[PDB]
Every structure is written in C-alpha cells, then in structure tokens.
Image (cartoon, coloured by chain):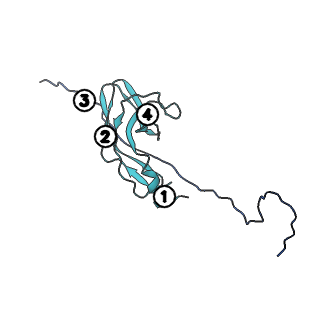
C-alpha cells in the first residue's frame, strides 16, 4: 500500500476546481445530465491523505429540476470524481443548493 | 385579521465525500540464472 507521505504528494495534483450537479449517476458519459452550471470549488493542501473544501459553495439549481449526483470537474475538463447525494431532491421552483463541505480522501 | 402567509425557497444542506484505496502487488523470486543470449557450453582459460 501507499505511504502517508506518498498519498500527500499524489493528492497535490488532482486539484478539483469546479463542481457540477447531476440527476442520474454520472458513471460513464459524464458530459450528460449537466443540470447546473460549473460553480467553482476551492480545495486545501493535502494533509494525512485528505483534502477538504476551503469554504461553503452555493449551487444555483434551476427551477423544476432534480439533483441526485454530482461530479468534480478539474481545470482541464476531466471528471475526476462522481458521487451521490443524501437523497434525490426535487427543486420544483428556483433555489440554491448549499454544499457545506466536500472532502476527497484516500485513507480507505 | 389577515392570516396571509408567505413562501420561500427550498434550501437543503448535504455533505458529500468520495474515497478510494490502493494496493501494491509484487512478484519476485530468487535468481537462478537469467535469460541469456547465445547459451552455449564454454571452456574458460587463464
């Protein structure tokens, strides 16, 4: 397995910059179901093989939309991480989604 | 009396995290020679 020192070095190159929400699990064809806009997200320096978001980000979800999954698109338009939310939520009207904290972790 | 109400926006908060793992696999064995070129019998001399 990798070392704590090894994980910290490797994580310093992912550098996610933007986050996009999805309605269907974006496994394969990540360019589809791009419900929201690429809101920017900032990550901190690696520490014990773990990066965390620097601050809370707000997602401007459009009206009459359903979001269940997300994706962390990097600088060079690559989907580096998929993922599901707590529960599929229906934004029947205009609203904003609050992402309190998103953390990428390799200690598993 | 009015009783008139208002309406807001749907605000939700969730914490999402995706993780992965790593494993290193190695296969080695004690050297018993090695793939050589021109494997022929030899007669050394000093």
Give the residue at x 86% y 66%: B42
The mark lying in front, picked from 2 and 3, is: 2
Q: Which residue bears the numbered disc 1?
A: A6
Q: How many marks?
A: 4
Q: Which residue bears the numbered disc 3?
A: B8
Instruction: Locate the N terminus of chain A by quadrant.
Output: bottom right
Camera-nearest residue between A44 and B9: A44
Spot the residue most to the left: B1
Residue A68 shows which numbered tag? 4
Q: Are marks 4 and 3 on the same chain?
A: no
Res A89 quadrant in image: top left
Q: CA distance from mark 2 to mark 3?
A: 20 Å
Report x, y in % for residue A39.
34, 35
Q: CA distance from mark 4 to mark 2?
A: 17 Å
Give the residue at x 36% y 33%: A38
Q: Alpha-carbon neighbours of circle 3 within 10 Å: few (<14), some, or many (≥20)?
A: few
Report x, y in % for residue A24.
48, 30
- The tint chain A carries is cyan
Disc with the residue nearer the chain's start (4 vs 2) = 2
Report x, y in % for residue A37.
36, 30
Q: Are marks 2 and 3 on the same chain?
A: no
């Amino acid at each position: 397995t990798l070392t704590i020192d090894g994980k910290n070095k490797i994580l310093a190159t992912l550098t996610p910059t933007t986050i996009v929400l999805h309605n269907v699990d974006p496994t394969a064809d990540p360019t589809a179901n791009k419900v929201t806009q690429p809101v920017a997200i900032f990550f901190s320096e690696p520490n014990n093989g773990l990066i965390a978001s620097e601050d809370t980000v707000n997602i401007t979800v459009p009206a009459s939309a359903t979001v269940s999954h997300f994706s962390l698109w990097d600088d060079n338009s690559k989907c580096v991480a998929t993922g599901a939310l707590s529960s599929p939520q229906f934004f029947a009207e205009e609203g904003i989604y609050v992402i309190s904290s998103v953390s990428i972790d390799l200690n598993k | 009396t009015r009783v008139h109400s208002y309406r807001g926006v749907l605000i939700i908060t969730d914490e999402l995290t995706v993780e992965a793992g790593s494993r290193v696999s190695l296969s080695g064995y004690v050297s018993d020679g090695g793939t050589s070129d021109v494997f022929t019998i030899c007669r050394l001399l000093d």
